[PDB]
Image 1 (cartoon, rainbow over the protein chains, first blue to last red):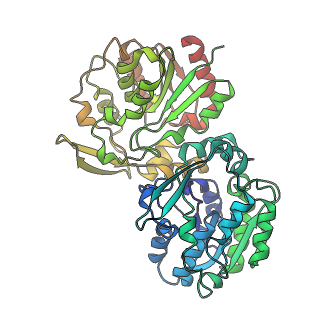
Image 2 (cartoon, rainbow over the protein chains, first blue to last red):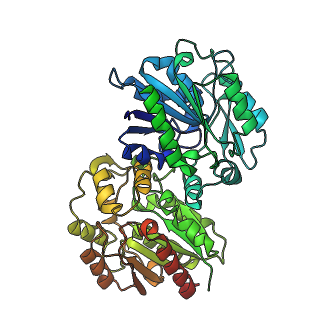
Length: 258
Length: 258
């Protein structure tokens, strides 16, 4: 059994806290874990109106990767939209990445536009329920749509099978976030030399009520991962409903990719 | 059997998230709960360097009370230093407050300075271990001392008996905080017609590794509460390690004080 350094990356609106159970589980098995707040997330001091793109939003992951002592690789694990952080980071630091794990998450490709998987998600799941929307204007004049996720969305669609304790936590710390979709739509594609070349492991459940099965199979068919692990039951937040399951999958990820 | 509106107030450095287990436990009995972040705490947008006194730090509680419609009463439950928030609020809004519950908490009086209980706490527990200290100057020239609580202190003194998931949570969302002690020491005394007149319930455990047995007993004798509940075992954070027991006691506070 390899021991590895996981870097855990939350989805927009969330923060390092989503990982509060998975992190000590990986550590009991002797792994090093880093759970990072992205910009304007968790207890990051920035607000979302000071952030101009998904690449800026990824700053804390990139900064973290820049300081990582040479020879060291990490396994980056991303939930939901954090798939985009993984692609951004692999195009800047391919050298330092053993593998990217996609945890009910967007799976960008290199053929299409980075906003491609976002587009397909919003076709798959177009009704965000009691979610509220807002806009501000970025550094070069783009209208950025932000969101405060709805509590009924949170209950039923992301945290479907979670504990009340965990659902209540999530309402206590959820923050505004953005897909920066229209800025993604204008961004150079992810590259083959960087993102294209890292190992990619995909983890999901068919019980997910926001990243739906037809969408998630579509992702797997669109850009074939190296490994696909399907967890039975649970919900979108497998790191909360299937913590040990995920800890064991991640061990197999460390076993195959170091 | 009475249902109440509980208003849950975390201590400094923390945020509303500390009540994530107690809130749904209370809601299960039919109580309404509100859990608020104080300034510069939890996910509040401010940093501590813009906060000039413990009263300013109290703004979101005060604003919340200010906005309550007439005829509506709350029970404020406060942990550690939040005893001061209770006093501050009760002097401003005695008419919206059914009781104040002190949860391993500073219990101010009306007859010494508002800093008295903080001074006595610091005599009792002068050494805060790996805790870091910083300073800034407030708008009126005072030196404010702030702190980042040490992880060892969090592990062993605050979250002694808590779960690995809860402890990890704390590390993930803990923020800088301040007692505003020098400012408290220049502050007018709490009034009899406000703070002085509310019902006060004091809840504690002798296994608390930071508010120690002698300090707490001393509080109890210096300013006699209406009721004293002693929970067996647990640790400093009873709303986490003894959640159901605290929910049960809170029901009775609601029964007495309506």
